Image (cartoon, one colour):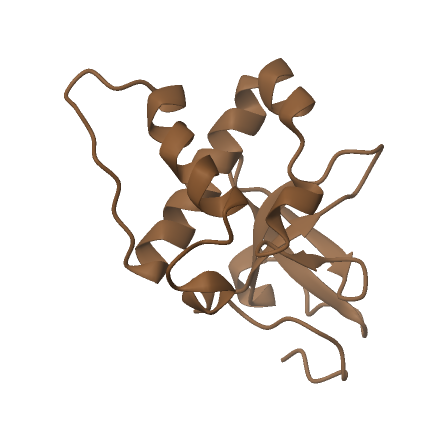
Length: 135
């Protein structure tokens, strides 16, 4: 599936915007994951990090998660615990893909864990770069 000529395939980490101004992280999935129907021509099914719901989104409107600082929004991050949770799960998936590790201490909070993950992302996901995030 997803041979319509456009960007993104199954497993790719993406930012999507479906309403208002906010970009949220997601992973492209098979239509089968959704228990809906095959995606319309030009579109991808994505599964949102955090809530795990599904949306059909134009391939031309999605952006790679690797374009990170461009689409991350610190204001929304500080406003919404739902966004903080979304970013954690998204960057955790990224981190495991890249074989990256960060120091941790017993007692660490969601924000404690996110701090080194955000620094890694904003920094261009070194050492792997964006290639580390591929399925």
